[PDB]
Image 1 (cartoon, rainbow, N blue to C red):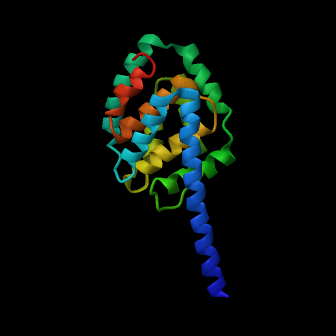
Image 2: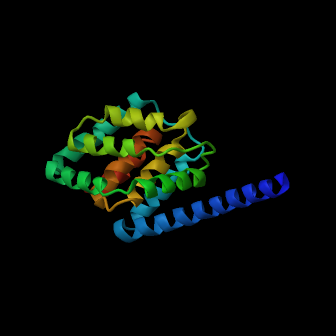
Length: 194
């Protein structure tokens, strides 16, 4: 009955890939619907950039993100951040884990994926405070072989888990860009009036 078992294993892996593609297409339609054209286009470009790429060093991600953190704190305040923190608190951890697994698959991540709700809790902490270092450390540790695909998969799972609103979206995308490619952060800035 190993013959039957290999067959079911391959059929399940195939259908998993199928679900991953369906989830990503629904994700881009979602982002388009609540954030707009430019936002879904940003997410698509960044997921393409991250597939087959290596995260930047955490030092560079933070020096990049600090620039973002400083323009952002010129226009938006701590009420604006607390809003995103409560949005994150509404995430369901089960669905976040499943969607994480599927996004990872869709982005070329070949390894095993575990529930990283703790990185989401750190996100809440680092959005209420301005201490992002442990957040970017945990994010890195999430990225096996330094794969950016894991990073943006996790980000997408979090955004899918909850209405972060354009500002939360911008902030998450900006962290991801800091790890994957600092280029996307100027577009991110545009999305909220720099």
